[PDB]
Structure formats: C-alpha cells, structure tokens
Image (tube, rainbow, N blue to C red; front, side):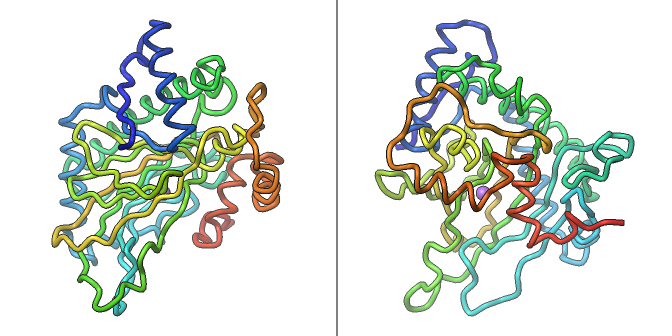
Length: 329
Ligand code: NA
C-alpha cells in the first residue's frame, strides 16, 4: 500500500518523463512520507553480494568482529558494535552493526581539519567486503542525487535545488544492521512498539533482506513495508520535513521483533547535506496549517538546523551516545 515509484527517468533528461516521476514523488512525500524506488539501476548482483558478505561478517565470532569495533574508529564514526547483553525480553530493535561512511584519506581537507564524521572506514577482513561496500556506496549515492532532483521537481523547484546548495558534496552515512532472532515474549509484550523514531536528515535509502519487519506510521495508520526484490525503501528525514514547512513528511517507523529463527539484515543509507551546509527554509512553498507550534518547538530543540551548520545539528542528536565524535587530541 506504499507507492512503488519507477525513477528511471530521473537518470535521463526527458522533461515529461521526469515530470511524471516528480508528480508521484510529490504525492508520496505529502501523504505517506515513504515509498519504494524501482528502476534505480543499482545492479542486482552487487546487492546480493553485499547481503552475502555482510552475512558472512556477522557470522564471525564476536571476538573477531570486535577487531573492527567503533571504540577503535575515532571521530569518523565507524566500526562494529555488538549486541546488548540479554534481558528477559530484549528490545525489538536489538541488533549489532557496522558503521560506515565515505572513504576519506588523511589528506582530505576535512580530515586534516579534524572535522567529526570524516575519515576512514574500518573494513573487516572478509574477502570482497571492502570493494563491495565501496561500490554499493558509490551506486546508492548516485540514486540519492537523482531522488533529490525528483524531490526538487516535485516541490516546484529547479532540479538542482539541493545539489547547488547542500548536497553537491553530501554527507553519506551507511550502516549494516543485523537483527538476530529472539524468543517470542511470554505473556504480554512489554516492549511492543519500542524504537519508533524518525530520521534526522534529508533522505534514507534502505535495502532490506527477505525477512522484513519494517513498519511505518502513516497518517492513515500503521502499515507493513514488506521487502520487494529490486527495490529500495525511501523515506524523508526531519530536516527535509522542516525546510518544506511540513509539506513533505518525516514519518515515524520501527521494526518488528525478529522471531523468525534467521538473522535479519537491513542496510540504511542516509543521504544528508554537507557537514558545513547552513540549511534554510525553502522559499516559495504553500503554508501548511497547524505547524507553528511544532515548527517552533523543533527550532528550539534543534538550533543548529536553521541557525548553524548541518553537522552540528546532527552531532547534537548523537554526540551524547558517541563521545568519540567530539573528542579532541
Ligand atoms: Na533510522
């Protein structure tokens, strides 16, 4: 019941084919804030290899995986994180993972400047994994650029609206998440619905394996977003919602508890503004009713969003959980 949008025309230059995609993106963004993307051109064989090599990584013993743990990754925000210890019933979003981002070397200007969230990945010693990760990052980054063109066209803007201001050199945050299967809770599930959240930035592009469990809170009710082979799942973040004045939705979502007996793999890619972008409200959009209160409380809780640089807005969300990001020396 989520829209399935073919975005192939966004790689081309046909104004009418691009307009048709933009019209669908606009409707999906206004009404659900979530849609599937097909015709995106990311090779099916690359996606399968990524899933298999990710699976191979998480099947390593924990002592091995900890060789690449985030505690070794520094301010770039990278590496492996293990499962929480056991509770009577763990959270439905109980997981391990691998934090990744753009591969930047020691001579990159942001690395020499010491800017948080820039630097090198920790690459586990799984044959093929490093190259596969970099190729997938490259290919899905291009999908992100094209989707922003469709979003710009949908809003009545020039297709390069975001590229020219904020995403020409975007902040790319990529994660491999693995959710092990859990016992079905005994009695009533205290943990039900836990983990509901919205994303922080512009665009999320999700690859999910065949297990599924993604659930989306649309204005018309909670819906399942099952895996569809050949698709990514796309949703918008808080920054995009707020810079459109609430016209395009940042929609809450969560994952159901995996009790399927097989580990569930989910790979989100966050396509965000440059760290130093100074994001501003988009001009020329219709006013959306009932947003002054929400708009003002969000501004107060996210001062850097419209009064500073995007990276400080994002660090304000995550620095408390990752003290290495603002660590000096
Ligand atoms: Na998320």
